[PDB]
Structures are given as structure tokens and as C-alpha cells.
Amino acid sequence: IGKHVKGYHYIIANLGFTDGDLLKIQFGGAEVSGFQIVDYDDSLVSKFIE
Amino acid sequence: TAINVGNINNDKKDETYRSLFQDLELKKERRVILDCERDKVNDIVDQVITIGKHVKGYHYIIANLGFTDGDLLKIQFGGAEVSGFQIVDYDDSLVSKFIE
Image (cartoon, helix red, strand yellow):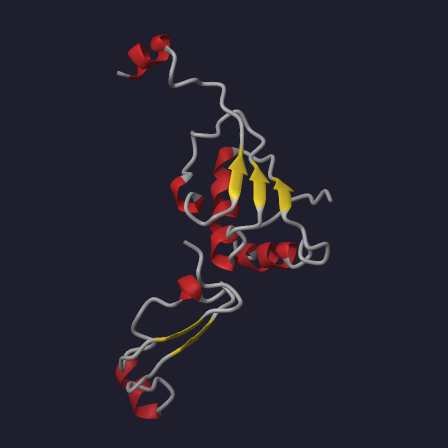
């Protein structure tokens, strides 16, 4: 429908922000916020991901 | 406002396309002609959706003899009007016998 351009603002209320496929509304223009509990920045996680 | 869209590679495709429409944003362009082969139509149209240039306001013209031959349902409900050309008429009774 096209409601994701500059103007809209969405919140994903779950602990898996990077889990969902987000690139689809990455370039749309709207801002998107969310939450993450599995931080891919902590060094222990990188050892697990590898 | 004629832009040569032909000479582009496949690994720097998403970068040049957004830069093209941010060049078509200088004029505040709402009316575009595409004039491309059907394979390149959907690659443009796909990027058109991801940057968000298909809402109420825009209007495009697909300059090729196959308007229904490519996928159109994706930009169907965005709001923008889309024009094009069709030579293979699917209402003729000679084609319907060929299609069945």
C-alpha cells in the first residue's frame, strides 16, 4: 500500500529486532525502532555465531 | 530529463538507482518514462517500491509493447498510476483460442 515513506514511524515490540527481515523497509524513508536482547556486538556472541 | 539507465553493473545496482532518483528529486519529478526491456522494467520497478516512489502522486509510462507481459501486481495498490502499451490483445477471440 506504500505506508513506509518519510513520515511514518514504527515500533517492533519484541526482543528480536535483527531477527526479522528488515531490509525490505530499510530504504523506504520511514523510521523504525525496536528492541534487541541478543547483541551481536558482544564478543562472546561472535564466538558463538562463527 | 533523459538519463542513460543502460550502462550499469549488477553489484553496484542498488547504489546507483537510489542516486538516480535523488537526482530525479532535484526537479521534484513525478512523471517518468522508462523505455526498457521487460527484464529491466521489474528491476527498476522493484527499486521504485523499496525507496517509496509509487504512492499517490507519481505516474509512470512503460514504453514497451508488453505491458501485461511483466509483473504488475506489486505496484498495483501503491497509489501511483501506471501507463503502458500492449500489442497482444487478450480479448480477441483468436488469441483466446490460442491461449486455451
